Every structure is written in structure tokens, then in C-alpha cells.
Image (cartoon, rainbow, N blue to C red):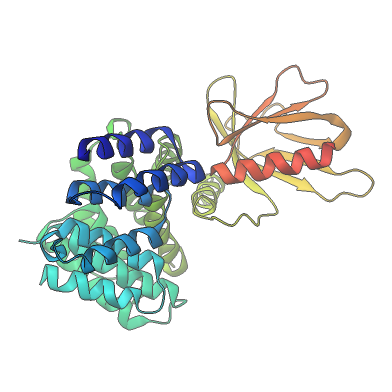
Amino acid sequence: FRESILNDIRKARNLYTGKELAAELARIRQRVDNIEVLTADIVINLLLSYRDIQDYDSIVKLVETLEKLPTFDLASHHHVKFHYAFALNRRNLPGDRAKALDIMIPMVQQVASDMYCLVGRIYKDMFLDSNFTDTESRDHGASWFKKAFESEPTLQSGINYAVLLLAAGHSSFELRKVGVKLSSLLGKKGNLEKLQSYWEVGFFLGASVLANDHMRVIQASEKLFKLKTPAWYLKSIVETILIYKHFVKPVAKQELVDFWMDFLVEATKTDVTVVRFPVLILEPTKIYQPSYLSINNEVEEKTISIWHVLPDDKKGIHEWNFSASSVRGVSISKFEERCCFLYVLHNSDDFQIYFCTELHCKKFFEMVNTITE
């Protein structure tokens, strides 16, 4: 019965994403909410499955019900408390972040980097979410990431520490000191081609951003795209980059750095509101080509505009403008839900267009069906 629930959660996380996953978890919950004894293995894998669709409200409500269930000892389950605080911090209703800190700070005060870094992230988020006015939260966040960094140096704590020093007005060391240590950690990790886990690539990206290393940023951003990085994770990297970009005081590849920053920030949006989409056109060479696309309110006939950002090969055609009557149609890829096929007249090939999220692709699909109907 336990094993059945566990096996079905794992199968659920593999088969489904989005709404389809939420349906499956609610089906599994009926069983979970009637189980003879509710163990921590079930709880943990439930919380991971809800995190896959950023359902922080379900995580909080489940963990609160375990706190009242007298025979579950929440205090003893530090990883469950970690995920609870994580969810409270992302949900951020009145008092959520206060409660997260009241959970996390006593757990820390041997403590692992992730625990120090979550507390640091709560402060970081308070700082960002205050429109950069909460300078006390900034300084508290810096101190927590600093402790992590000195206790167990990692790129994650190091980049977050540096970014908050940058926001505090750091011509300076710790800042160049954190910089030296970041460079030897990057040395330890080795070439980007051998880093396969999304979490290694994400922290490589961040330190590459801090280093102002353009080619690595572009390379690591693309790798983060190909790896189907979870939204929960990309969120935290993006937050770090937004703070960096706000506070840091052309290079011929600036255009591709701007594209990738725009792509990865757009990828954390759940409400799609954009005049234009940063996209990757998959070429028959099997290279993803950074591009922009827009659906234009043009007089007489609506149009689709598509253009390459900084193509390596500057020769040939890198811009298209299609009138509504020029479009045969659109089809979402049967294999890649981020991808929409666009079919146009007098073009024997197609455009295989890859968006930053599934929803962005679906919006494009719907808008093109509207102009062709």
C-alpha cells in the first residue's frame, strides 16, 4: 500500500507535467489521505511532485496538516521542514516568510550549505520583492550566504554572496576575494561540456555572469534550455541575475547575451504578456538559432515577423515577414511541447520554433490559429 503510493507518484512525475500532473496527484491524494500510517517517504515524494508544478499552496497545507496530526513528529523530519520553509517562502502570503525563517534559523543555529542558502534566499527574496528597498534583508542575506561560503565554499553561496555585496555598494575585496575563490571552484568543476546536471550548469552560468564571461554565459544559457531545467530552479538563478544586472556598473556578442538573459527571465513568467517572443529556431544543421518573433497588428492584413539575433553566418536570409494569407498553419510538436511548427506558402521546409516555456508555445499556436481563421 505504501509501496504502491510511492511507485505511482514516481510514475506520475515521469508521465505528466502541468495540469495533467496536478490531476494525477489529486487522485493519489485520496489514497494518501486515508493511509493507515503516513510515512515521511510518501510525504517527501509528494512535496517534490508538487514542487514540479510550483504548487506551493498544496505543499504548505499538507505540511500544516502533519503538524496537527499528533503522531507525525515534524520536528524530527528536517528535510520535510526544509521543503515546507521553501514553499512558505515562494507562497509568500502575509507571515509566510516570517514562519519560514522561524523554521529554518533554529534548525541551523554541522550544518549543510543548502540550509544556510535557503535562509539566505528568504532574505534575498525579501530584498528583491521589496523593490530593492529592504537593505536590512539584503545585509542579512549576505551574512547567511557568507557563512555558507566560508563553511563550505560552493558556487551557489559564492555567487549569491557576491551579488548582495554588489547590491550593498561593493575597487573592493571581499568582492575580488570571493572572485578568486569562485575562479578555483570553476576550475574544480571543469569544462561546461562535461557538466550534465541542470544544477551544475545553472551555478556555472551564475559565476560566468558574475565574471562577465560572455561566451560561457551564452553556452551555459543554451545548455540550461536543452536540459529542460525545472522552473523552481531556474527561478532562483534568474533572481540572482536580476539583482546582478540591477547593480553592476559594447562587446560584439552583447546581443546574444541580451537574448539569453531575456529568454531565461521570460521562462520564469507564468503570465504571458509579451509583444514579442525570444525563441530558438531549430535549423536542419541541428543548431538552435536565437531569434525573435512577433504577431503584428498591421493594417489590412496581420503579419508574423521572425528574425535571427546575431547569426554566425551573416550571409543569407535571416529575416521573414509573413502575411496572414501566407500562413498555411501551425502544429505543436508531438514530441517537444515547447516547440511549434509554422508552415508557410512557397517554403518547402518549415520553421521549427522553440519557446521558453510550454505556455509560451501554446499562446503562439492559439494566436496563429486566430489570424488564419
